[PDB]
Length: 122
Length: 97
Length: 177
Length: 59
Picture: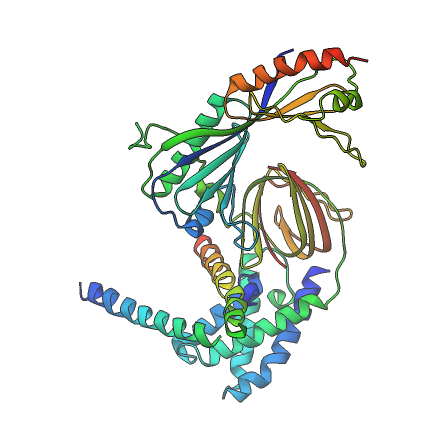
């Protein structure tokens, strides 16, 4: 039910920008190249199948080592989540998340939610 | 929000406008106008293209709230939506209001 | 009974002007929302502590449960700020307030205390029972409730928390139910 | 090393473009408010673009 939404969105977007391309002075061939370029990169990645693809006071240095690795936070081969928040709450080190309209990619698979509620200790 | 240009969908598109950057759509102008159209289109489709809900749990590492956008990074976190069971030890969450 | 310290609010001047936005983007465990707070809130897991780092090179370390733990946590926050690269100094790590809690282990009659000590004690129930016995000779505000535990707040040094509890102990012993 | 001259120049052109953006800031009580309204969809969008570059580099 996900490849379907993507096709759905790609179709709608392509159809909805045609006039803009035309108003800007563009050949419909370019539009088709866009669709092809677009569809192709997903097929090359192979994350899922697609219909198109099939076709002292002075020195502070006295302290030695606390502050963890900032670089650990970024890999970009990890799991990224695009969503909206309704309410984010915290008490002491207890956080509660009230999220919505989210697209998740966990363990390689793609998931979607209208609402997501979570809990975590910091 | 030029938020969703960091999506498979959005990047594949740009890589198209960049093949035009080198051959036909030289720099911005056309390409920029197209991206603008994309912003309106992706935003519109998200808010009214349906959706399904759930509830879950996690462990945290960092956070960043600026421009009304929250960016978290959880560690050793597993999220389950409906039937689907899943695991994760490093997840980044970007959330707009 | 010996009171146990629960919070040390301590402050230290880092000595130089700090750009808050840069610190928030690179430091881990950091939140800097300008509309709500006027400072970066930074939290470390090893010794529990929440610290507000101000823009003029200042840092208020809260949440530490002993004196040495607070000095060490402030040193760690300073080290984290330095590794980013801003010039860093450590000056005047001075404790501001320490809150301590203890239990007398006996039921106490708050109403009676107000009758014989109206001058130093103020109590209004209104859905929140809690007698406040502001004491002048050792400056401390002690909140004594009905169960028994006497919390003590406002002491700048460890000795004051202990001295006040010993001073208030006879009064409670007299009103023991 | 004419490449270093390019870095000094194209980068200098980028700085003048940034100055042009600083002029856009003004146009984009009401006026003050509008600056913050546009800032909301400026730096956050820039951060999203930087994440898009980081993911592309990882690819």
